[PDB]
Amino acid sequence: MADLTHEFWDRLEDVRSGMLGIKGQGRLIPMSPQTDDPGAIWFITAKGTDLAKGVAAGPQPAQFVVSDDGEGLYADLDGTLERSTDREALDEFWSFVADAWFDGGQHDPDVCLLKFTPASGEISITEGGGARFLYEIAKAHLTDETPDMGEQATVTF
Amino acid sequence: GMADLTHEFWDRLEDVRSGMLGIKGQGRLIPMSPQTDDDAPGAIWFITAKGTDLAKGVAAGPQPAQFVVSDDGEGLYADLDGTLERSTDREALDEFWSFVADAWFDGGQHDPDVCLLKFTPASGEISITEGGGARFLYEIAKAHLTDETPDMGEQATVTF
Ligand SMILES: [Ca+2]
Ligand SMILES: [Ca+2]
Ligand SMILES: [Ca+2]
Ligand SMILES: [Ca+2]
Image (cartoon, rainbow over all chains, first blue to last red; front, side, top):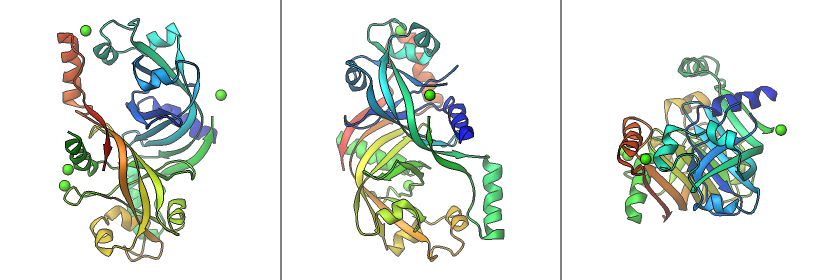
């Protein structure tokens, strides 16, 4: 549904890490997703890496996987990864953590802004916190019904 | 070392509450609860329903599978290739059974819908880091203060 897509973007904003990769090329690796305003997931990386070199010629079909317990967001997304030369996006998603890795600032020659546009994906969202979890377990013994911790669906972006 | 990074994977995987599991060439990865013990490493165990796609997918026999992990609290990130299969091991079923499993399956561990799945990793690209707590904040702050890149941790492609 539309609410599941809006909830995905809302919770993705606080997700510190995710597993990114180009389809048919190696395995997935940990990356720091950046989002603000929705539409795409943005990443800062080195030009010498396999992901940077893989999207040098053009946009490639890619995969991005999220599994965050803190936010309760679980997603396997199919999409498109590409190198972005956008100055505004680069400046927006630059941070104090990024400066530690790249000593030359946001305009460092080794810096590479990747843009992941999701196409579709299977998403699970954990509605409620520990309070609902505690209630659903108590309810499970009272009713013999399986706990409903949230929504689950396959979405087209 | 390769063996040292492998030992540390099993060491931290116990505290990982969730992971993304799936059979290769069949749908997308879905969230599952990995149950392991670092005293007996080698396999990652999952308790699921017989009516699910993962259960039905491995009913005929063992199938190539993928298990992806990404945990900031433990600093364990891994994309693993392996084999998923049905297990009729009552010892493993009883060891990894929990209060959460009682909620989903009203008839205990000997419930008709209960299905124990065993994922044996073959290989994978694993990253081990200092986490995202006190040490991570210090390491980023120290990187700025010394003109050195942060010493996050180790990364390698491992064969189990
Ligand atoms: Ca669109
Ligand atoms: Ca341990
Ligand atoms: Ca232990
Ligand atoms: Ca510096």
